[PDB]
Image (spheres, coloured by chain):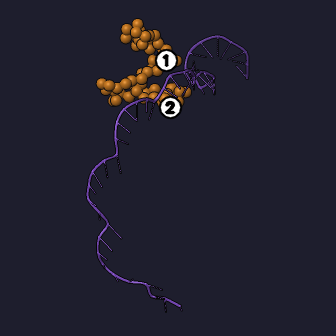
Amino acid sequence: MIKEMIEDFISKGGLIFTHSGRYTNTNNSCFIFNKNDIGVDTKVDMYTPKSAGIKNEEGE
DNA sequence: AGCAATTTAAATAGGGAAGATAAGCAAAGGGTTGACGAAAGCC
């Protein structure tokens, strides 16, 4: 399910971003979602504390 | 005690043999490098 997942994300810290300083330093935790660069094939990152979240029936 | 000459021509061709093989092993390791969240003494 998808809504189940979006809400699983929201019960947790719940951040969706396209740019971050988390890659520069893992202790940083700055997450920035730019609106202008979202396109058809724009890959999009998300953050949860310790990457928490349930999987589906196909294990994703 | 330096003086030692000039031109001219330097071979055309025919051949550079194929047949064989070119190992099989067994190794090639992991040891550290984790930030948030949550109890839990402690100024």
Chain under label 1? A
Q: Element under label 2?
A: loop
Marks 2 and 1 on same chain: yes
Crowding at label 1, few (<14), some or many (≥20) Cα neighbours within 10 Å?
A: few
Left or right, A31 with respect to B37, comes to left
Chain under label 2? A
Residue depicted at 32% across the width and 25% down the height: A41
Left or right, B25 with respect to B43, comes to left
Residue depicted at 49% across the width and 29% down the height: A23
Instruction: Give the labeled residue for mark 2.
Output: A24
Instruction: Give the labeled residue for mark 1.
Output: A51
Sequence-wise, the earlier of marks 2 and 1 is 2
In the displayed image of the protein, which residue is found farthest to the top?
A57
Q: Is residue A2 above or below residue A19?
A: above
Image coordinates of residue B11 in percent, x first then y, are 29, 63
Q: What chain is the purple one?
A: B
Q: Is residue B41 above or below residue A23?
A: above
Image coordinates of residue A55 in percent, x first then y, are 44, 10
Residue depicted at 46% across the width and 10% down the height: A54
Q: Is residue A4 visible?
A: no
Image coordinates of residue B8 in percent, x first then y, are 29, 75
Drawn colour of chain A?
Answer: orange
